[PDB]
Image (cartoon, rainbow, N blue to C red):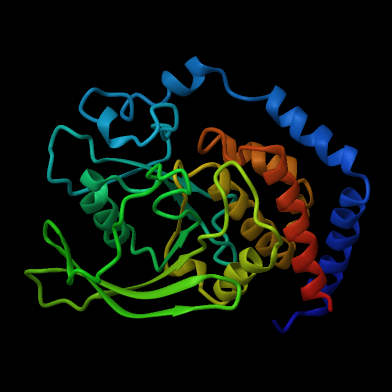
Length: 302
């Protein structure tokens, strides 16, 4: 990246703070314990997520306790089912309207019966990127995510939507990059390009062995303009790994944009949790945020 003097100074300032915290890990543990003490109560989730908890929609939730708030859920409009209130388990995550800072749609891994819903959301919200932080199935053979994207059996269809894979590339850091095209079957308007990035080495309720692959996702997305549209980020529930990734991406972009408040990662995670329950699930994930932010600021200032 080409940085201004102001951006380079801010990266150095942020690096001293974040590296100071990893050198004093009790400070980071106290922050996460404080976040856990300030968690929302069950009635605050349930009474403010009325559409997700509706009988028509409960089977559209992978996890009964991970649902979007009514205030910032993504609504399918138009929607095939006129009684569903446009429901998809998906949350708009943002810290501002700056066009220098990405907004995210944090969502669950699609279920077989919500895959048309997922791809209609991609088109309606014109999302240019999908970041997928799960395998389809874990090493216990528990299904974590529906296969909404693989085409080896033949080109994929979801109701009126057609999906094509133009190419698949892998990286030395284990990322899989798929160039996807999505369009309606019965239209003359052009297809929509989506870059799908899958990282299969981030365990559920866990952390990767190192920060290199997660920072490579951020490095590949630095030059994607936020104004193109929200970045979809999902794992299985769309809160633990998803929240962790969004916190790393958001914090680095905010430092580069001159937002001093990015140095308060606990405040960032608190704001994420006000937009989707339980974003950043574990203390190891919170430490991973710090380690990835430090490592990326070291690269930015190298």
